[PDB]
Image (cartoon, coloured by chain):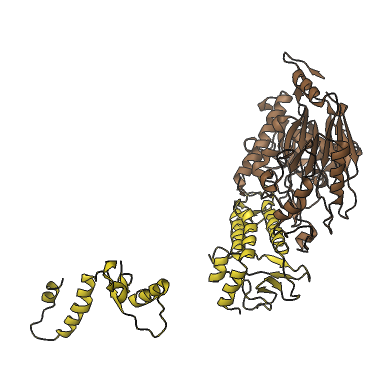
Chain colours: A yellow, B brown
Amino acid sequence: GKNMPAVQVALRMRKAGRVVKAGSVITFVITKLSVAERAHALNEVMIKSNNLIPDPQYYLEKQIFAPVERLLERIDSFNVVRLSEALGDVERFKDTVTLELSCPSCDKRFPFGGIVSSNYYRVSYNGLQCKHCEQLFTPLQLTSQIEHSIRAHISLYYAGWLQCDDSTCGIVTRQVSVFGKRCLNDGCTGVMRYKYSDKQLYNQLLYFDSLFDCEKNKKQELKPIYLPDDLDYPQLTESSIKALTEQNRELMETGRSVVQKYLNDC
Amino acid sequence: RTMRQNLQEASDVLDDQIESFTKIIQNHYKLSPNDFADPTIQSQSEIYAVGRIVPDSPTYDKFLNPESLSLETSRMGGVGRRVRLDLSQVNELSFFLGQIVAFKGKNANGDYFTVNSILPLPYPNSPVSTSQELQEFQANLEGSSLKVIVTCGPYFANDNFSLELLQEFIDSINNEVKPHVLIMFGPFIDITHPLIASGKLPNFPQFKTQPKTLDELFLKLFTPILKTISPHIQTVLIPSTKDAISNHAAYPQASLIRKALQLPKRNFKCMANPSSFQINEIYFGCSNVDTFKDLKEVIKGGTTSSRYRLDRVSEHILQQRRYYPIFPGSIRTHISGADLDVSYLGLTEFVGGFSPDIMIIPSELQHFARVVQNVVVINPGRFIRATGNRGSYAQITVQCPTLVEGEEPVYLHNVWKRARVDLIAS
């Protein structure tokens, strides 16, 4: 429909206010850029004050030359040259680890996947709901847990583990030599690297941000938190998803600001 | 400073510490560079060696002994090659991770550097002040003594959020003690707090509009209470490695932003963790990481053991010229820890090489008041216990103000002669 001028015109009519439904006859004339974008509705072109002249090139070619070429194709002494002269984000979060949340009432632990299906939570109109106990989450009982996980992760980060590149040895440690990249094992040429390097923290924090992304939730690009074979595998419809996202915009935005507290400093 | 950890810059800082303390050793002991050499290599002659103390194995047991300690060299000293240590000759030693020590000895065989003697690290200079400034401080105190009150977090129990003890303390300091300076370290709302960790956080009927984050939880919970401290009481704020309000989760730690915390400008200031400052003449040093609890020593010889542990650790802090000489940093396997920002390790080093008059380092241990090497170490303890019972806080009674020889007359501060540190329950 993007290279058909018809679909373009119908969508423009709908945006402008003209109601077009399936089974409609739309009448369109090309103005003077591709073939589709130049198109407009015939009544729109008709008003002479809009300065929407027909394209001489497109009409003289398509509505004349090709039909005339087909019609005169196999008639003696026809020449095409005479006729032509007379006319003319999925990879980034592959390693992230899920944000685990807890029930204020029933102490149940569960992973979270935005506004999607879940055997453990149900995104309601009034907010998130723990299916095992149906109790509603207050903003704090959510955001405090989230940033608890956040600060545990940053604690793991500044714990500053170190990794030996050389596969045959592969020591993990926190001792740092004054030649940081050189490994501490006798004669090891493996190059020392932090296991929890800053890039992974930034990936985790943007994964967090996606978990509370209203647009990504509407567009449904969010990474699936359950593999097909999981016994805890949950299907909600996109219309319900959009309605729940719009109703829960404020909670999504507060959860977003909580993560931005550590994003803008990341 | 962004939240970035670079291995090479950290290595640079660790080389720098060895270099600087080697120069300090060579200056105070008036030794020449030629008398220092590489301790990791075989040598038939005694040498001076300076380095850090590390385990002989990068994957090392929790516990250490004097037969499994090694010395790492600087970049130019021994090309960063770590040499094991033979401590059998030295009867008395107090070693731990991250320190720096100066050894006399010799490398007999190549794989071991025998310690013949230990060169004790000189204690840093105490600060001085001129006569006129001391007289001005006298006028500021008007003959009266100085009162500084010191408290630490957290301020509410593990299971409830009642701040009656804090309110009683504020009433007391406003009406009876009348202190010139009040000190409060973080964390205020801890994030290893069990209820906030498990999300069991109930509605507050004492808030008209319920909060939404721990920031607004502070604003409605703590800002009311903190606004009752008397304006005549200048109060400082210190964050910690666990305060959820701060957007800094590492040590060294930046200050809080007083505006977003919404405290009046009249009597509150936000300082750094760690930081040093002067109240009149007294030169303070504040740090809020529990060196005392986590710093684990390896001790040989009776005399070192006989001493109080707190004195030993305080003298080690003095010798290392940094508030947290532990490296690698602490871990609570993972929930929390020291969270050392190694590339900024310089920020915790003593301000200009001056040991402070008072050094207050909150610990999860018991409270105490001890003076060592003429510096006032204070641990006012936790204001409220885990159960929620009473704690303790520090009250410092310094009398209103030795002469140093020199063409310019200055005066070494003597706080341990003049200050009375009382550890009163909350």
- In front of the other: A127 or B109: A127
Q: Quadrant of the C terminus of chain B?
A: top right
Residue B6 image offset from top left, x and y in percent: 60, 47
Tag count? 0
Residue A214 image offset from top left, x and y in percent: 57, 66
Q: Residue at left 70%, top 25%?
A: B27
Q: Is residue B156 above or below residue A243?
A: above
Q: Is residue B89 visible?
A: no
Residue B237 image offset from top left, x and y in percent: 74, 42
Q: Quadrant of residue A236?
A: bottom right
Q: Is A59 on the left-hand or right-hand side of A101? A: left
Q: Quadrant of the N terminus of chain B?
A: top right
Q: Is residue B216 visible?
A: yes
Q: Residue at left 90%, top 49%?
A: B390
- In front of the other: B172 or B128: B172
Q: Is A107 on the left-hand or right-hand side of A9? A: right
Which residue reaches farthest left? Answer: A77
Q: Is B62 on the left-hand or right-hand side of A118? A: right
Q: Is residue A222 above or below residue B75?
A: below
Q: Quadrant of residue B239?
A: top right
